[PDB]
Image (cartoon, rainbow over all chains, first blue to last red; front, side, top):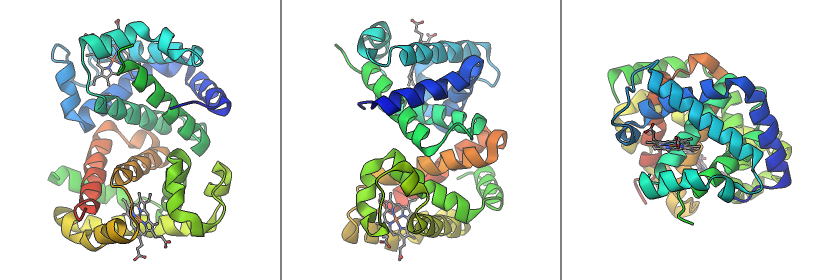
Length: 141
Length: 143
Ligand code: HEM
Ligand code: HEM
């Protein structure tokens, strides 16, 4: 989605409040996705996907760190995310539905931990932001 | 639905404030997915997030939507039959594209996460995703 100036500032403030918990929330979002949408597990056949798995916690930190980088580059996400799109679109060929599933589970995780920060307006801006990340990661450009 | 799913859905719903969650769910639908405002023009001014969330008609309708979902929890093995008439209404009279039923369900799940916090565990969410998937499929059935 195309982000407004208000969307960008909303995302920066919300993700800033995530702060040091970013890695923790990324792993929780992954666990939520694997349990609610078990077809997503077929992309991780080499992972231990049980609860508390070291691989899932390490991967949640990677995803969260990538989102933090995307927030810093919210005005030039295609360039900033080119290597990541190369992995997800060219190598892994992730079906775009899966980005909607992870994005939903990220929002649920933020709602469960930061209810006061997760206002309707911020919810709307984060949804647009994650859809824009998802579009880049599913494009070959 | 597993028996575990049915117990989790029934248990959690008994703790939901339906009026609060209903208004918050419909309001968030309209804020987050703004084209859905077109279906509710009779509700008045939906031109900003705070105008939507404080609109008394949005809150009243949201209560009716969640009350319909709460009534369906007594019929979890026959959601198709329970929602057949409402499926016709949303298709033939309201012309709601069925993708929007999935969106409403996902907003409801986020609102439950807001309300229940850590208690809305990954396992509890998975039962509720089955719920909103089944509701959306039942409302789409007559399309
Ligand atoms: C917001 C969306 C996403 C972000 C920011 C993201 C981020 C990342 C990052 C940073 C990596 C590691 C890249 C590297 O080490 O070079 C990665 C790898 C990977 N991603 Fe994603 N990802 C997203 C969505 C998804 C989805 C939806 C799936 C599939 C359901 C997926 C499947 C994978 C897999 C299988 C790997 C390789 C993991 C491994 O072998 O260790 N990603 N992702
Ligand atoms: C879980 C999904 C949904 C449920 C359970 C649900 C349920 C209901 C119910 C119970 C009514 C009242 C019908 C009556 O008065 O006889 C209604 C009406 C209506 N619904 Fe839905 N609905 C859902 C999704 C949606 C969505 C996604 C939209 C549009 C984006 C929508 C648009 C409408 C409209 C416009 C009305 C008429 C409101 C009025 O002017 O009074 N519904 N729905």
